Length: 355
Ligand SMILES: O=C(/C=C/C#Cc1cccc(NS(=O)(=O)c2ccccc2)c1)NO
Ligand SMILES: [K+]
Ligand SMILES: [K+]
Ligand SMILES: [Zn+2]
Image 1 (cartoon, rainbow, N blue to C red):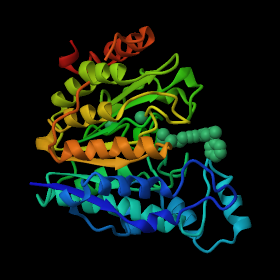
Image 2 (cartoon, rainbow, N blue to C red):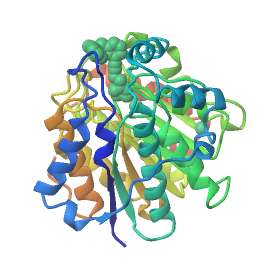
Image 3 (cartoon, helix red, strand yellow):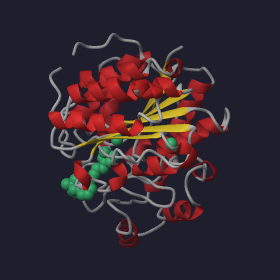
């Protein structure tokens, strides 16, 4: 039918009390929402309500210890908040943090439900804190709970356990948590494009490399597309979709598509250093829309240039609403060609469409 949108101002309450210029800013989501309104995209959408995730829903991917620890931060005074934050890789916590993480997850569940119950065809979730770095047992890189991973499981819980869910993660950073959660799982195809730099780029693990293809029955169902050697843009991203993402995805025949949609590969992003354009993101989205009968949920992850993320995510919602793709390239950077050839060599034994 239509396009769903979920957004809740309360998720702005998560904040960094010791550094109010930390790039994971509250107004990330409010700038995005504002922009959807200015471009008249908001009123074309069906407003999906936000909700808290339950602790039972969190246990779909996370350990009870981790849930309890993060939940306990709710009552901590600043000294202990800071102490708990420092126990993870790149985490700040405020008393509202846990609530905001629950809201982000819950928001996505409701959206996935609207899709799967046929209330909407596709949807956007303007949410924070992000999630794809979060592991089963720990918080990481601004992420408390793995929103995307939880949503895949939630979708499976209201349809069937083996429901084919594709997760495309085009945030500039590798989704270590998402990869790990489904690494042995053939029901969830994880595809991530990320800056790698041989382990120099956050989160600095060889897990992000192209030769990590999955374990056990999940072998082949984890696809890393690692970038090395500086700036990449629309041509590199269109190529990777063309040669890898779409052919593998079609072959997987997903019943639902989740996008971990960080916009930190955007032109202008201070952490990403890439130059994917709003138009670029629109085309990526428009391609994914051809999958799973159009059942596509776009979930905000990273992205720290307020204008860039506002422009890029708006363009994605434009495509979900069915607007025509904007016009678009250039020869690939040589290392991007190597990256793609590497992935192709690594996944050709698992996907006939690559042969
Ligand atoms: O988007 C993401 C996460 C991005 C990140 C990061 C990171 C990790 C370690 C060090 C720094 N240094 S900093 O300048 O970006 C900085 C960061 C935060 C506060 C102050 C300075 C950044 N995942 O999808
Ligand atoms: K990624
Ligand atoms: K997998
Ligand atoms: Zn990121």
